Length: 186
Ligand SMILES: NC(=O)C1=CN([C@@H]2O[C@H](COP(=O)(O)OP(=O)(O)OC[C@H]3O[C@@H](n4cnc5c(N)ncnc54)[C@H](OP(=O)(O)O)[C@@H]3O)[C@@H](O)[C@H]2O)C=CC1
Ligand SMILES: CCc1sc2nc(N)[nH]c(=O)c2c1Sc1ccc(C(=O)N[C@@H](CCC(=O)O)C(=O)O)cc1
Image (cartoon, rainbow, N blue to C red; front, side, top):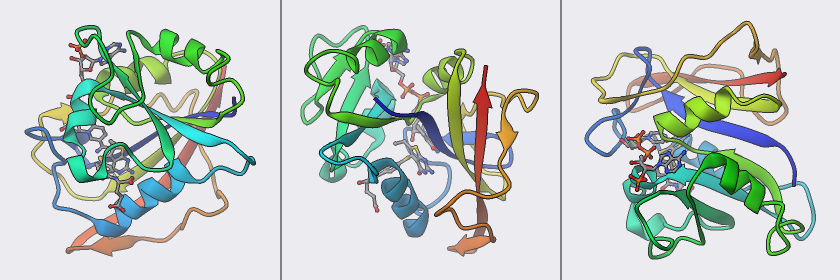
């Protein structure tokens, strides 16, 4: 299995969600960024795996689930089987990551992308080892009821360039945003 990664879009006040959806109106090219990053795999005959909590799964429009071209894993201790349209179910982050090492997945999975929500981001960001964060900074405050955990910049370096990630200010629907990639190894 390849690299471990988180991807998120976050407002200035650290918001990632409100009432089961995003705090901001749809940013179509920001969504396309999410799909390009999470779907694109450099390794032949492999796909990337997405790991998400149960509320994040149900926050994706049903017409867009499962996230196409990716293996979709949902984290839940209450569910007894994957949701309709999902591929796998795990009861912990450690279990999910171990699953990628099993024979059914060992030679199929390239990158792993954690796509939230707040509890899984926090646990992933604090788990020793090599991890990158692909963070979209939405440069406004938005009322939110779900927040991104603290990024400890003593361990996560903001990278000064990354191939394929635009460096300049983007804007859609009157909302400016910019892309960032962080990396730790501990
Ligand atoms: N802006 C962005 O980039 C993103 C925004 N969002 C937004 O955030 C909201 C959803 O996030 P959030 O509310 O944090 O919810 P989550 O997606 O984290 O879902 C929480 C549920 O997932 C299960 N769960 C979470 N972590 C684990 C774990 N490690 N092991 C086992 N089960 C786990 C639980 O289910 P159970 O009780 O069944 O055990 C828990 O009740 C929505 O508003 C969504 O739109 C989400 C992702 C990214
Ligand atoms: C899955 C939870 C996350 S992580 C994330 N990271 C960044 N940068 N931006 C976001 O908005 C999200 C979200 S919320 C989200 C993301 C994608 C989608 C979605 O429908 N994606 C489809 C459609 C993409 C498209 O509209 O281009 C896909 O990836 O195939 C829905 C909710």
